Amino acid sequence: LHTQVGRGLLGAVVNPLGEVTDKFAVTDNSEILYRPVDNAPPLYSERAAIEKPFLTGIKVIDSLLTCGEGQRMGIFASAGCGKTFLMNMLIEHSGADIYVIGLIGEAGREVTETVDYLKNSEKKSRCVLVYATSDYSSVDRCNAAYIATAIAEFFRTEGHKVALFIDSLTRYARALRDVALAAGESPARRGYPVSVFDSLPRLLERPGKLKAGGSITAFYTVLLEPLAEEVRSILDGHIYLSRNLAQKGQFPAIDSLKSISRVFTQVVDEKHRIMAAAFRELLSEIEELRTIIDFGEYKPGENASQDKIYNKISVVESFLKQDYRLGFTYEQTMELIGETIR
């Protein structure tokens, strides 16, 4: 019910008991303080309105799905689809002050995959990893998410721009269902006033930007295969990783036409907003021609409008794809997308 926080956790891997068990980086600072894991959410009067962009360095996101400081964004994918590789990019190419990663219920050579990644990351000195493998109990698998959030909340009160990753909400929700059985309750025959099922919106309401402090921009992963629609109505947007786009060699497999950032128009300016709308129309026209092509109905020179759209497919695909080791500045992204829409 209380856990370690502070700058002394930077570079450390913490287990569901709040103990440091490993380090992927060692830091000068030793500050270790103690805070409760069940913090209340910010009153509406303490939250600031989301109005500043959280740049990710990912071209399709920064242009068409622009995130905001304090936003909570879902990442929806069937494994895999590359959900883990997209998050690695989000860590590597964004510009947060501090990254806090929570691996819930993952097999556990998965955690070493991530520790090893963090061990070689340029952001190693500003990450904290909280983990829970599959051997740990459902109470412990749940507690990893609560501990990661409390750690992130401390850094936000200190004024830091924090990014939080919970992977995954699905296995969290599964462990959450197991915990509910201990209380005698199931999704249909649920408890009141306290159900573990309503622990889900409370955990998700903790991110945001404080008027008197920093911000927590949170990314929650959801594994596709009903959990997704409730999380969908709680969050401020969702990124959809497509089984189709991965098989065709498009990474990141983000389907822009099925993804949205609801604060988009509050966090980019007008000259951005016009280019994004024009590009979204170009994608929609490319898909419609794909189905004309698959139907064997496209013939060059027959329809000048289709021919122009056809010759744009390669430059749009070139903009969409991104080498996972490459990050792009906002100016670079807007310059590239404008040439695409030219």
Image: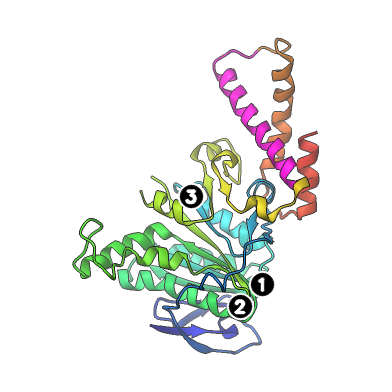
Please, what secondary structure does the residue beneath circle 1 have? loop
Q: Is residue 80 left or right of residue 85?
A: left
The answer to which quarter of the image holds residue 231 is bottom left
Residue 78: x and y, percent?
Answer: 44, 46
Q: Is residue 61 visible?
A: yes
Q: CA distance from mark 1 to mark 3?
A: 25 Å
Q: What segment carries the magenta color?
A: 272-298
What's the magenta bit mostly, secondary-structure-wise? helix
Residue hosting label 2: 25
Residue hosting label 3: 76
The answer to which quarter of the image holds residue 27 is bottom right
Q: Nearer the viewer, residue 323 or 90?
A: 90
Residue 310: x and y, percent?
Answer: 70, 23
Up the image or down, 208 lies above or below 329; here it is below
Q: Is residue 227 left or right of residue 111?
A: left
Residue 185: x and y, percent?
Answer: 21, 64
Up the image or down, 81 lies above or below 169; here it is above
Q: Amino acid at mark 2?
A: Ala
Label pair 1/3, CB-CB below 8 angstroms: no
